[PDB]
Image (cartoon, coloured by chain):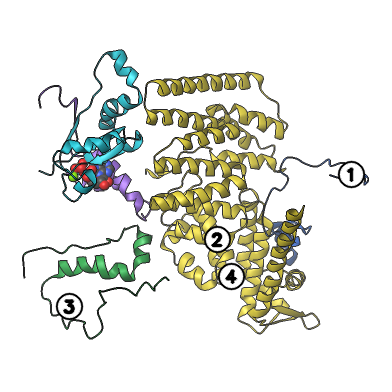
Chain colours: A green, B cyan, C purple, D yellow, E blue
Amino acid sequence: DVLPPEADSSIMMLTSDQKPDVMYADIGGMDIQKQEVREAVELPLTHFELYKQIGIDPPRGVLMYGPPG
Amino acid sequence: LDKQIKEIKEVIELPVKHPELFEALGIAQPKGVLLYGPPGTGKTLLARAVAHHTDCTFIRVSGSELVQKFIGEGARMVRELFVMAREHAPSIIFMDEID
Amino acid sequence: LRPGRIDRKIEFPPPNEEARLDILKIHSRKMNLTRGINLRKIAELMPGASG
Amino acid sequence: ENLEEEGLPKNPDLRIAQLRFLLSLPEHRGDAAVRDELMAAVRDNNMAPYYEALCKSLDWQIDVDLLNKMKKANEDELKRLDEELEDAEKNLGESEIRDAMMAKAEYLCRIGDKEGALTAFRKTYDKTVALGHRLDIVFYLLRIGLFYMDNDLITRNTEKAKSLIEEGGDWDRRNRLKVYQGLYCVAIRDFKQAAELFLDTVSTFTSYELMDYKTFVTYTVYVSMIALERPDLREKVIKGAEILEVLHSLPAVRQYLFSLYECRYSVFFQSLAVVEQEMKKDWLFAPHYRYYVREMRIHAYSQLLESYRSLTLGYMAEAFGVGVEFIDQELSRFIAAGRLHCKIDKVNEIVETNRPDSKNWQYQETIKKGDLLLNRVQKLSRVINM
Amino acid sequence: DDEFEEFPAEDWAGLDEDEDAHVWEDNWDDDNVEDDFSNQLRAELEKHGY
Ligand SMILES: Nc1ncnc2c1ncn2[C@@H]1O[C@H](COP(=O)(O)OP(=O)(O)O)[C@@H](O)[C@H]1O
Ligand SMILES: [Mg+2]
């Protein structure tokens, strides 16, 4: 037998009730970081064709690093 | 890097493709190349290009312990890489100093 | 650095004004470029820049 | 100022193809200026194989002295390139090998040796490891295909070019291929695709080896008026910033475009007549000059009738600056063809418009194109059995 | 194969110089015999005294 791809996964997605209550407006003073994450995570997710038309290769992953807190 | 492309060809391309030029000259075939300059100047770009154009297998030796299982279960010497380098001759062993 | 070990040492200087234009001419092909871009001026706008 | 230097190499020079076509026309066969400029291209580039075909097809007198001095230099240069390839294959490396056989291909292509150039380019492609260098050979073959209208060459290399641009995301080369594709689409009467491809590259045009930018915008406007709807025309052509800038230096093409959009039908017919003569002398638009003018006349008649329930013959004749008899004959021809949704009441000289549904037009195409497909299926089974 | 030499193969005498060599959706309307539209329009501009 072949199982459905979404089956057999010990890790589950985030449900609507598991969505954190933290807003963007809750975060203060991270415009450079907010922009880069938007341009590299959420904008390619919705504008993948505009990246292809322009010629930018969207980053597959994003590494966020820095001092704790 | 037109000047640099010519320089690296005379040392990595010609000995592989035309060993007779060096035998006629009576000189030893070159074996070691050092590319030096500021980071991002094309050293890794040119080293990969020559290996691509000469059909020489390109091996990057970063000393990573993540790749040691492929090099060999011993991992006591870096010369254990020569076993997999000989099997893929012609080969180019490339190491980049991060510094 | 001892003679006989490294048979050739090749220098990779930072690209000058003309070499920066060639590198600029190479990586800009992968983009949807409007006709008439003055890549020469942008190269002049980047002194001492790497490829 | 460096626009022409940005374009790909001018091999084969597509101007010669236009020059050769112009002499094939009965009107321009005896044109001394067109002969002189063609001979200048032949003499400068030593196109000995092209001179033989030029004199054979056009029944010219072959200058033995000029041919021999052109053949000798072709032999001398080919010997030089053969020596360079021999030197490269013995001492130099693979890249210097490839540059040696590349220059042999360009010289053969330059002198008009089409069969030799295709073989030389094929051999160069086999041992060319650089992807962009491979795609330059394909663009060379596409230019050769356009030069001789070799459809098998164009279609095969256009498909090969599409693959190469996918592996290496070369948007610059992708933009050039659209201009190459659009030129072929013009040559094969695919104005719907030619308009789409030209409009995409109107702001990214660097293919100066094929044509001038003013000529490219001229073609873009021409294919747009016949293949674009009125809402699509105003957003892309009428309000196009790049097209409008060029139209400042091209008052005739701008007048032709805006006459139809602004419903100036008398001027549009005058402009359409001017456009017709341009396309007759143009090697790309010549096979389709009758079709394009007829379709443009259909557009103007349909545009005038679209907004009105009934228009008198005299008003339509007055609008187009033509006689009533002209408009009656033109309509009766077009209504019979099914391309105008109207009928003429000749006793009262009133043209009443109809609104046939899209279902009927789709059904005829399904019957038409399905029958064309079925004929291929029937013919293929005939080949299979025996 | 039993080729049809019985039927008189009328001599070709055709133009082997790529007379058409095209692939379009060709229709009968392009072959209608008529003057160019410029001549038709020029022959009617002066019919109105212009
Ligand atoms: N001279 C150059 N020409 C074209 N691209 C270059 C050049 N130098 C650097 N690059 C680009 O920079 C990137 C990384 O360069 P790299 O070769 O890693 O630098 P380094 O020479 O310090 O190793 C490559 O992907 C390459 O595309
Ligand atoms: Mg580096």
Three-letter amino acid code at disc 3?
A: Tyr
Q: Nearer the viewer, mark 3 or mark 2?
A: 3
Mark 4: secondary structure = loop
Residue corresponding to mark 3: A24
Q: Position of residue D120 (x, y in %)?
A: 52, 32
Looking at the rendered structure, which numbered label has been put on residue E9?
A: 1
Badge 2: residue crowd in 10 Å (few <14, some 14–19, many ≥20)? some
Q: Tell me, yes or no, whether dots 3 and 2 are on the same chain.
A: no
Mark 2: secondary structure = helix
Q: CA distance from mark 2 to mark 4?
A: 27 Å
Q: Nearer the viewer, mark 2 or mark 4?
A: 2
Label 3 resides on the chain identified as A
Label 4 resides on the chain identified as D
- Check if mark 1's residue and mark 3's residue have beta carbons within 8 Å: no
Residue corresponding to mark 4: D264
Mark 1: secondary structure = loop
Up the image or down, D166 lies above or below B92; here it is below
Three-letter amino acid code at disc 1?
A: Ala
Q: Position of residue C37 (x, y in %)?
A: 33, 51
Looking at the rendered structure, which numbered label has been put on residue D193?
A: 2
- Residue D225 location, quadrant: bottom right
Q: Is residue D76 left or right of residue E32?
A: left
Q: Position of residue D350 (x, y in %)?
A: 74, 82
Q: Is any part of residue D145 visible from this angle?
A: yes
- Residue C6 location, quadrant: top left
Mark 3: secondary structure = loop
Q: CA distance from mark 1 to mark 3?
A: 85 Å
Q: Position of residue C36 (x, y in %)?
A: 36, 51
Q: Tell me, yes or no, whether dots 2 and 1 are on the same chain.
A: no
